[PDB]
Amino acid sequence: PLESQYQVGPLLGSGGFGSVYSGIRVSDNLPVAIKHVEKDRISDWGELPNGTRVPMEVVLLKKVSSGFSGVIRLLDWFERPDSFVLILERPEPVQDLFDFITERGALQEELARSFFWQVLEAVRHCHNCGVLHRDIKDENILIDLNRGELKLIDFGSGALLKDTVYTDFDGTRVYSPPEWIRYHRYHGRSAAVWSLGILLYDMVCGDIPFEHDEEIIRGQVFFRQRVSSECQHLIRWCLALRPSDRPTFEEIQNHPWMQDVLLPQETAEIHLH
Ligand SMILES: CN1CCN(c2cc3c(-c4cccc(N5CCNCC5)n4)n[nH]c3cn2)CC1=O
Image 1 (cartoon, rainbow, N blue to C red):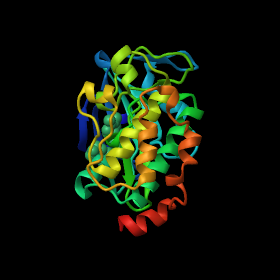
Image 2: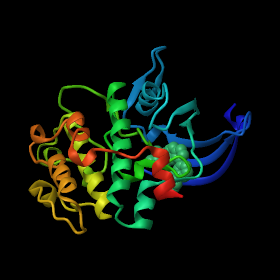
Image 3: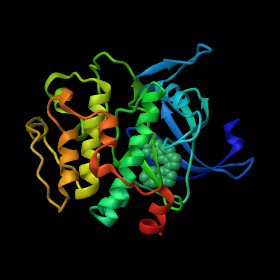
């Protein structure tokens, strides 16, 4: 009975993902996030090993929630008559990257390097677990303000990772690649790299580079803030129009702009405290 196991707090947010509340596990006072999703609104369904009908999100979270890392872990879940309820890790104090950027404006490159690196490690972890996130962006990353650690959230638009083409997409359009816009097709890793380019631009410029379909399709990157040449180069590389022209994760992390990253804790002490 989830009713008695958790003390429900205030609404943290709601939108396309459903409704997410602050909570506390009664047994040990562990801070949690309680996410409700209506079944009528669940588009993609999946199956547990033990053969049970469940939201793909839950399948993806399980595959990815084993071990430590930069992904928010699924602690438990429940099925209700017309909804599923997910119990998720909740860091505290925390702020999502979108609000963080809005507040501080464009980030110092040293900070953006540390954040971006951690996002890369998290996404690599998902891919190693057979999971494609598909909605990488500032709103889907949490910053643990005390530890300097980022955490990927919201796998509700995700899919099992495969090497064949995807012909469906339900992530954020302004983060979707030109091949989706033009052809309604993309491959997982290379689409992910494109969204990482948007994300990195967003961090160092304090806003998204493209707003309309035609800008995405043109792929011309204009910098509105001062950004080093190395960083501009990495961004333009991630945002190559031809998917095959984009860097692999390894090539991103071996890029000269990516060298000498701060540890998360160093990052918090310098930039967060
Ligand atoms: C799209 N989306 C956004 C909220 N999300 C989430 C938030 C949290 C949080 C959390 C903690 C503190 C604040 C906070 N919100 C996130 C929304 N923006 C305000 C801060 N979320 N902890 N754990 C979470 C797990 N998922 C579920 C989800 O699917």
